[PDB]
Structures are given as C-alpha cells and as structure tokens.
Image (cartoon, coloured by chain):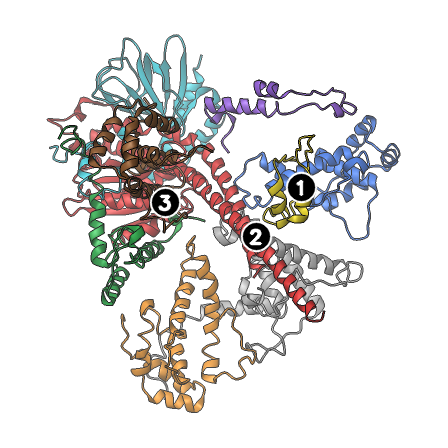
Chain colours: B red, C yellow, D cyan, E blue, F green, G orange, H brown, I purple
C-alpha cells in the first residue's frame, strides 16, 4: 500500500520498529522527531476515513495542517536510491543523519509549510526540497513560452 | 481473502460511525437554524399581501434564482428544485422571453448548466459558509439588480417541519416595468394607498421592490438552508441503517468464512497425519 | 450432539420430581452459528440475559 | 391593462399544461398567510393588528390601538380604520400603544404600510429598543462623520445618513422621561 | 480500555485510586463513545465537547515513558488533578508536561499521608485540592 | 450506502439503462408457463440485437422499467408499456351492470 | 497496472518508448486515485477533473483488439500522440477509432527511421509532432 | 413468500383456491415490491397506498393460530373476502376477528357447495357475493 | 438529537410507563440482605401478573 502510491523505499513508517529507537541511546532530538513523525502519520491514517468520502472541507484547519504535514513527511521519506537509477530516472541520494533529523524537525514544526507537497517526492534532504521547489516554479513560469514556435520552419 | 472481509468490516463500521455523527451534526445545526427561519417567515408577508403574487406574468426579461445547497449529502433536494426550475423555465415562456439563469450554491451551478447552459449567467457560492445575513442577501439582490429584468423568479424549499420541504416559486415585479402595470385591475388597486415617501411613487416602488427582493432572497436562502439540514439529517439515518444492514450481513459472512477456514485447515492437518499413520 | 444430549436429556421432569437447569452459556466468538452454541441452544427452554 | 392574469391559482392550472405530471405544483408565498389587503374585517372595534417585522427578529405580532411611526415627513399616527398608506421611514422611534403602556423601538430606516383593511406592517431593517443604546458612541461617531466631507456623492450620502441617524438618536435618547 | 478487563475488579485496587479511577473509567467510556467524532470540530454540541475535551485530557494523562514506573500516590494525585478538573487550562499537547509540573510543584508531604492512610481523607482532600491551585501549570 | 440521490447525472443514466437491460434479459419460458401463467415467448436473434441496441442508444429511456420485465422483444416492451399505463386509469367502475344479480 | 510489475525495470524497454511511457504510467497513477474518489462525485477541483480527463484518454489508448499486435513503433507513436497532447480534445468514446488515423495518415517513413534508431531523435521529435497535427481526426 | 416455491402441487391444488390465489400471490408480490421501493417513510405517493394497505390486509389475513388447521372451503372463502373487496373497511387490526366473522356469519351451505364442486361456479359466485355483503364486519 | 420535550404526549406517557416498569423489574434479594441492609422480597406469580 505504500508502494502503490509510488513511495520507494516502501517502508511502512509505523509498522517498522527498532531497538535503537530508545531515547537514551540515540538522544532526545532524534527520538522526539521519530515519534512526532509517527504521531502525525498515524493521525493522518485516522483521518483517511473522513477524507475519503467528504473531502477535506470540514476539518477546522487543524486537521488540514495535519494532512499537509503528513503528506510532506510521506513524500520526504521517499528517497531515490543509487542502485535504482536503472528503474526510474534519478541519481541516488545519500542523506546523512543530522540533515535527516533537521529536515524532518523542520517539516514537523511548520518551517516548510509554504513549500508544495511534490517538491518532497524523491529528494535527498531538505535543501534539495527547496531546490526542486524553485526549479518547479521556474518550470511553471516557463511552460507557456514554447507554444508560439516549434510548429513550423525550424533552423534547418 | 479472509482479511479482505475484515478490512471491509472495518470500512463499513467506520462509515456507520461517520454517518451517525453527521446525523447528529445536521441535527445540531438544524435546531439553532430553525428559529432564524421562523423569524424570517413574517417579513415576506407584507410584500406578498402588498405587491400581490404574480408568477404568470409576460415579462420581457426575467431572472431566475434556484437557491441550492453547497455540500452535497442532502438527499435529492437540489435535483428536485433543478427539475422545478426547468419545469417553470418551460412554463413561463410565451413570447421568446429572455431569462437570466442565476444559482446560489455550488450544487446549483453544476446542474443548471446541465439543464440550461446558454442562459446561465451568475454563480454565487459559499453563501452558507458562516451564516446567512441580510447584508449578504442585499448584495446578492444588488447583483440581481445589475440585470434589469421585468420579473424575478425565486426557487427554494419551504421548510415546513423536519420531514416536509415544499419547493416554492416566489416572484418580484420591477416597479414601473411591470409592478404598477400588474396592479391595474379594472383601474388600479395600487392608487388606493397614500404614498408618504420623499419622492414620487416611481422611487418608492423601486426601493420597495429592491427591499422585497432582498427579503424574499434572505428568507429563501434561510429556509432552504434549514431544509438542507433537516434533509441531510434523514439522509444520514438511511446511511446508518444501510451501513448497519451491510455490517450485519458482512459479520454473518465473516463468521461463515471463519468457521470454514478452521474446518478446512483441520481437514488438511488430519489428511496429512493419516498418510503417515 | 450426542455428548451434549447425554447430559441434557437426564435433566427433565419424571413422575417423581424434576430437575431444572440454569446453565451458563458462553457464545465463543460472538458467534451464535458456532456449533457449540448452535447445539446447546437446541436444548435450551429459556434464556436469561444479564447485561451491563 | 391586466393582460397577464397571474396568481397563486392560475399558475397551478397553466403549470398542468407544461410540467410533467410527476412534479406536483409548486407553492407560492401567498399560500402561507391568511392576512390580505382587500378582505374586510380584522378590526372588531378599537384595536387593529400590527405586524412589526425585521429580517432576523419579530419584535411584535400582537394587536395595538395606535402606532406612532417615524415617517420621512415626520412622526405620524395611525388609528384602526386608517387610510391606506405606504410610508418611507426616517431613522427614528416607533412607539406601539396598547393602553397605558408603550414600547419604544428605535429603528434605522425602512417602510411602514397600512393596508386597505386596516392591517399595518412595520417593516424596518434594524430595530433596537431604546434601553440598550448608549449615548456615548453616538457623539464620537457623529463627530467623526461631521468633519470628513469628501467629494464623492456615495460617501456624502453615507455621511448624511450618519448625521441624520445620529442626530435623531441623540435627540430621542436626550429628552426621554 | 474497551477490552482490558480485570475479573477481580476494584476489590484489589488501591483505595484513594478507587475514589478517582471510578470516574476516570466512566469519562473514558464516554470518550470512547464520542471518539472518532472529534474530526467534526467546528460543528459542536458543547456537552459532547465537554466529554470530548475531558477524555482527551485523561487519555494524554495516562501515558508513561518506558521504565519509569510511577509510585501509586503519584498516580492517584495525577488522576485526581486530571479528573477533578485542575487541568482544563492545559491544552491536550502539554499534559504529559503538566503532570510533570504537578509532582514537582505539589509538596512531597502530601504523598506520604496518601501512601500511609491509603485513601484521600477529607482533610487531605482539602489539602491536596488547595495545593493544585497554587501549581504553575505550563498553560497559555 | 448513499442511495441514488447522490449519484451523478450520467450515473443515474447508467443506473436507469442498466436496470432496463437487467429486466430485458429476462423472458418467459414456454416450459415455465405451467406454473407462472405467462405464456412463453421465443425471441429471434435479430430482434434481440435490435432491441438491446435500442435500449443502449437511448431509444427507450421514456419507458418505465417494468415494461421490459418478462416480455419477448421490444414490440412487447411497448405493448406492456401502454398496457401498464392503461391500468393507471382503470381501477374502478365495476359497481353495477354486472353479472351478479340474484335471479337471472 | 496497479498490481502489475516488471522487475527488469526499464533496462529492456524500447528507447523510443522508455521516454514516452515513463510519463504514461505517471498520469495513470494520477488517474487511479482521482477516479475512485469521483465515483462518488463529491466535490470538483477543475484541475483534478483534468487528470481524470487525460488519464481516461490513456486508458482508451491502451485498449487493443484480439489478434492485432502493433509492432513497436506504431505503439510509441500512438502514445506520443496522447502524452504530447495531440489526442486531447478528441472525444473519449472515440479514441479507439481516432488512432487508426495516427497509423494511417502519419507518413510511413516516420516508422522506418524510428525502428532504425530506436529513439526519437530531435530531427524526428519535432518532425513527427508536426505531422500529428496534419491528420484528420474524428470529432476534430 | 418470495422464496417459498412449490411447483409440483401447482396445477394439482384446490380449484377454487386456484381461482382466488393467483391474484393473492400477485398482490403480495406487488406489496413486497412497493415495500422494497419505499423502505422508510418520507414520501406518500397515495397510489401505492392502496397496494400498501391491501398487502397488509392480505398479510394479516394469511396468518393463523397454532394447532387450528382450517378446512380448504373455509379458507377459499376467507381469502375471497380479502382478494376481492368485502374487507377494505376493516382497518388492519380486526382482520383476525373479521375472518372468523366472515366464516361464522356466512351461510354454512356455501362451504358445502364449495367443497363438493371444487371451484366457485357463477351460481356460487353470486351467493358468495351476496352473503359476504351482509356480514357484520367488525371494522365499523 | 431532538430533546426531551420534543415528542408527543401519548408517547411520553409510554416513556414514563416504561421508566416505571423498568424500575419495577428490580427486586431486593433475600441473599443480598447481608451486604445491603434492605431485606428481600419473594413475589408470587399471579401477584406479578396483576401488579404489572
């Protein structure tokens, strides 16, 4: 169910567990981000029965913040692998641990709520999120320029 | 496949809780928005016993208002008044009458376009987003005044009780364009009144017709809102009864398949043990 | 059915006296179609449902 | 001159000839009231029925003996068998008389009918009873409105409504006994 | 809580917890009737919102933190403070730190009376009740 | 769950046409007339294809659903659609000039 | 296609279709969720209606008759004709018959070069997209 | 009744009961259909209300008491009195009284003629129409 | 979802009658009087029939 949405690596963030997810081995700034990500994603999975028939319009804009935060976290958990360049399109990304914890602590506490949800899809860390975001903005501001030429009379 | 039945049971169970909660949400919103309809039912009466009630008028130009709901779990109210809108936009036509089609509500623009897209002009929506106020209905009436028709046509559901909602056609005649002419009965019944306004009758009937349009529109979109709530309250108790009957049938089916898989696994174990014993 | 009816048939009224059984019934998986209560309920001449 | 003989009784029978018979005849807002203009009666002596309305409230629906109404010419009175009148109303005070007692509604401006059977209909927009009004904010808003005189006729008409409304409201809260 | 039973019951409960858990379980049962209806937040009933906000108080009250077992007087003071209503100021996301801000704030001379007597005596039911109003809760 | 009232217009169209062809696949059998009373209707193949093509194209949306139920072909559909309509007038007028006097 | 996989990846996809059909299964991934939600038809977004419109163009594109295997170059042009927009505004009931126009009315010389190279060269990327406008389409 | 079938006994049943029971099964099929169409009470069409009342009339007719089997001649007449008119005055509650009223008040030789003939002849139909008009129905 | 005083008078008479039959099915037990204080009552059959 993770993989049919295209999130690869298709790790379930909730059902996957570790013994290193103890706050007195990996610190508190790691444990708190991991549990807050799990809390937002389980809240969204609770929301998905009222989202699916009603449509995100009666949610008092506290649950809508939760849906947008969870969709950003869900896309940002995906990562293009170095060994999966053969499949989809993307050179792989190694995401160091501190950049992961800072990025998910940023998305978790509202520091990146103004960024779109698909700029998090298949990107390495949180500065690649913004670099894909501005690039997408340039793409949309440049999509409507090519409809006036390339229809006849090329330059041989 | 025996966890497909269990996840379907999960789905239908949370649906039957969602609709049991939305029935109570609609029942809460109906009881505080029932008193504002009853406070609004008085003010339409002086203009209807004053301007009369004249639906079958040969208006050169008309504006129709089908005021609908916005959210769409009402249970066939907006489709009912859309059928009434076409059944009166075929009835009133006798002279090649220009009609302006205007719908208030998001579920009116999506159906009246399927019925009459060529004459469809204005769309008002989010008119129930906080509450219905007379300033809002006045601004909608002023936008209906930017068309200068010869009549106005109002299609709304008359909230009688929490069960009965009747679609009502209400009309508003423009002052000197048809309103003073339709009172001309063997003479005139309008000239029995002493106009006490500042200026002549031509701009007291203008002000009074704009006020009657605002009052009819305000009472229409309050009464139709209470019909929307009290019909969603009974259209979310058929969802609970349907989700309860389907949960009963699916629970029976899941017990049948549970017993069958215990018996099937048992017969497999005995068949494997007897080939060695 | 016969291991249950070997018990529940000696609980009856003769011409001497009578035995009346108040038997606690556990419905196994909230399942009345389970064959343990579907066999037990055949003999049951009344029920007394205590509720919370 | 009455070439379109419309009504709550004619549209039902001309609607039988165009609408499909699956759809029952639509209602009309005259079906939901028993009081009219032409039908005589509704007096029975001294007291005539008043219908004080407002969009969000109905402040009075019982009968009174005499109404004092702030017309655009000035505060007039109606008796039971009064002449048919349609009165545009200035921002002023409506007083409903039933005997010794009286209720003092300050309205913001509307209309006030008296119908040919003598039934009256006070149709105002915002109507506050004179107790819950302060004499404080009116002076400050009047002073803010009495200095800003722009060129546009829109804001000049709005400010003139402010002057007349606040002047009459201070005049009606000042000399109260 | 809907499926966790104890066939012995409260006969083997610490008294002083039995005085307050008897209402804690009732309000949690009301919340379990009212849960999954809390996504309709703007469209209130204002009486089911009372059992909703109280059940959300009491759900975040009961959380612990992995091999920090709590002594029983601190538990019954915790569900006293949450049950009686001393923590309606605190929003639902700060009651894991509001209970930490009760044990550190209430003086530890009430805890040995509550352990010793093994019930909340009415002198103590005035003392620790008055002690929970001089508590500096992390509220806004 | 939701009923027909929360369907789209094209989905109400699909539901109506599908209810009509659900009834139109039924037919009375020549060997089941001894207990149903309805005589059996053999249907030719070209009649079947033309009739279902007409229901699909929208030639019979104005007909009710039960006019399609237990009939041979699309001519008998309209025969029963008229016969079905006619009984919506005549439900009465069997009071006098009968064959139920006493002496005759 | 929601449950169908090929575990060799795009290692052995035809290169004139590895670049066209990569954005085919993206728009059918967008089609598979927005069409089940609009089976109810609850609300409209008017751009989610577009990806519900274009994804249903591509479903009718991937239909095939029984014993008619289309070689490889007439499959990549019939998906170039839909993923580069040429079969948009062509009626959804008539895409299964509008694509015989793309096989017939487009020059037979554009398939010989695309089979020979295996990849849409820029001298063919624009020259074939200029000829997908020079075809007679039903509905038009 | 929608699921109960008996094919071999049909065209071998009682001839009078066969005359009066085809319309019985017909109007119960109509009753189950007009109950399945309007399952909950919001709309009163008033043309189905005849079927919705005649169906409950026949359903209250069909039920009987235990250990009291009825002869087929005292049963053909009692269902004649419901598939025809003769009981549309009695409301729904006294049909178990109206049935024994019809059976006791009618001439007991009608049952002998019906049992001997097997079918309701027009000579017997005339006297059955006569004697079922002059019965004192309890719904009055 | 409506309130107490929404329903009619003949229905709320059954609400009162059911609220006083639902109370009248209670019974103090003789074997409970050692841990309640209130004594127990054995009720005859026709007495129950008449009192209901």
Q: Position of residue G111 (x, y in %)?
A: 37, 87
In the displayed structure image, the side of residue B78 where residue B153 appears, left or right: left
Disc nearest the viewer among 3 and 2: 2
The first of marks 3 and 2 along the sequence is 2
Q: Are marks 1 and 2 on the same chain?
A: no
Residue drawn at (30%, 83%) of the image:
G104
Q: Quadrant of the N terminus of chain H?
A: top left
- Badge 2 marks a residue whose secondary structure is helix
Cα separation between marks 3 and 1: 58 Å
In the rendered view, tell whether residue B142 sits above or below residue I42. below
Give the residue at the far front of this rendering.
H116
Cα separation between marks 3 and 2: 28 Å
Residue F40 appearing in the image: yes
Residue drawn at (14%, 36%) of the image:
D4
Tell me the number on the disc at residue B76.
3
Residue at which label 1 appears: C8
Q: Dividing the picture into quarters, in which one does residue C43 lie? A: top right
Q: Are marks 3 and 1 on the same chain?
A: no
Q: Dividing the picture into quarters, in which one does residue B42 lie? A: top left
Output the chain of dot 1.
C
Cα separation between marks 1 and 2: 39 Å
Output the chain of dot 2.
B
In the displayed structure image, the side of residue G34 where residue B223 appears, left or right: left
């Amino acid at each position: 169910s993770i993989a049919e949405l295209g999130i690869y690596p298709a790790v379930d963030p909730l059902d996957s567990t570790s013994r290193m997810l103890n706050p007195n081995v990996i610190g508190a700034e790691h444990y708190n981000v991991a549990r807050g990500v799990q809390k937002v994603l389980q809240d969204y999975k609770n929301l998905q029965d009222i989202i699916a028939i009603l449509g995100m319009d009666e949610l008092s804009e506290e649950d809508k913040l939760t849906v947008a935060r969870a969709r950003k976290i869900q896309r940002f958990l995906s990562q293009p692998f170095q060994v999966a360049e053969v499949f989809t399109g993307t050179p792989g990304k190694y995401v160091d641990l501190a950049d992961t914890i800072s990025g998910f602590q940023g998305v978790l506490t509202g520091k990146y709520d103004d960024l779109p949800e698909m700029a998090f899809y298949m990107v390495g860390d949180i500065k690649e999120v913004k670099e894909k975001a501005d690039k997408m903005a340039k793409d949309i501001a440049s999509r409507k320029e090519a409809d006036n030429k390339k229809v006849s009379e090329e330059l041989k | 496949s025996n966890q497909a039945v269990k996840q379907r049971i999960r789905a239908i169970k949370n649906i039957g809780k969602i609709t049991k909660a939305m029935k109570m949400v609609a029942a809460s919103k109906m009881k505080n928005a029932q008193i504002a309809v009853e406070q609004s039912r008085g003010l339409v009466d002086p203009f209807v016993r004053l301007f009369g009630d004249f639906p079958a008028v040969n208006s050169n130009k008309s504006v129709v208002v089908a005021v609908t709901s916005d959210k769409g779990l009402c249970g066939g109210l907006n489709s009912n008044i859309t059928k009434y809108t076409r059944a009166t936009l075929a009835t009133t036509e006798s002279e090649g009458k220009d009609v302006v089609v205007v719908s208030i509500g998001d579920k009116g623009r999506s159906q009246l376009t399927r019925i009459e897209s060529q004459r469809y002009q204005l769309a008002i929506a989010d008119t129930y987003k906080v509450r219905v106020t007379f300033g809002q209905a006045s601004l909608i009436v002023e936008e209906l005044i930017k068309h200068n028709p010869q009549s106005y046509q109002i299609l709304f559901n008359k909230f009688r009780s929490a069960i009965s909602f009747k679609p009502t056609v209400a009309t508003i005649l423009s002052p000197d364009l048809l309103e003073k002419q339709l009172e001309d009965v063997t003479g005139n019944s309008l000239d029995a009144y002493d106009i006490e306004a500042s200026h002549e009758r031509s701009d007291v009937l203008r002000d009074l017709t704009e006020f009657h349009l605002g009052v009819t529109l305000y009472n229409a979109m309050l009464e139709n809102n209470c019909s929307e709530h009290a019909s969603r309250m009974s259209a979310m108790e058929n969802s609970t009864k349907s989700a309860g009957e389907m949960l009963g049938k699916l629970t029976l089916d899941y017990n049948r398949k549970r017993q069958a898989t215990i018996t099937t696994e048992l017969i497999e174990i005995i068949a494997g043990a007897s080939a060695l014993m | 059915a016969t291991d249950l009816g070997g018990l529940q048939e000696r609980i009856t009224t003769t011409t001497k006296g009578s035995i009346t059984s108040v038997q606690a019934v556990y419905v196994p998986a909230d399942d009345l179609t389970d064959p343990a209560p579907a066999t037990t309920f055949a003999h049951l001449d009344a029920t007394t449902v205590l509720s919370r | 001159e009455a070439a379109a003989p419309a009504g709550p009784k004619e549209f039902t029978e001309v609607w039988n000839k165009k609408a499909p018979s699956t759809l029952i005849v639509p209602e009309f807002p005259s079906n939901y009231t028993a009081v009219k203009a032409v039908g005589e009666g509704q007096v029975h002596g001294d007291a005539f029925p008043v219908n004080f309305y407002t969009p969000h409230s109905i402040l009075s629906q019982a009968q009174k003996d005499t109404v004092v109404l702030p017309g655009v010419d000035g505060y007039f009175g109606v008796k039971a068998s009064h002449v048919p009148t349609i009165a545009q109303l200035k921002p002023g005070v409506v007083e409903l008389h039933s005997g010794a007692e009286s209720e003092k509604f300050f309205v913001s401006g509307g209309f006030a009918f008296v119908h040919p059977n003598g039934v009256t209909d006070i149709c105002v927009l915002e109507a506050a009873t004179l107790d819950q009004v302060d004499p404080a904010a009116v002076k400050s808003a009047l002073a803010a409105a009495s200095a800003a005189q722009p060129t546009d006729e829109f804001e000049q008409a709005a400010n003139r409504a402010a002057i007349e409304l606040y002047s009459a409201l201070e005049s009606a809260v000042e000399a109260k006994a | 809580v809907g499926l966790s039973v104890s066939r012995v019951g409260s006969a083997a409960q610490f008294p002083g917890m039995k005085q307050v858990a008897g209402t804690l379980k009732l309000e949690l049962a009301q919340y379990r009737e009212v849960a999954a209806f809390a996504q309709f937040g703007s469209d209130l009933d204002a009486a089911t919102q009372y059992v909703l906000e109280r059940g959300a108080r009491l759900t975040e009250m009961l959380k612990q933190k992995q091999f920090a077992p709590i002594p029983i007087e601190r538990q019954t003071v915790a569900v006293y403070a949450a049950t009686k209503g001393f923590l309606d100021k605190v929003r639902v996301q700060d009651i894991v730190a509001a209970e930490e801000a009760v044990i550190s704030q209430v003086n530890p001379a009430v805890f040995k009376i509550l352990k010793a007597n093994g019930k909340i005596t009415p002198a103590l039911d005035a003392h620790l009740k008055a002690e929970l109003r001089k508590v500096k809760l992390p509220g806004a």
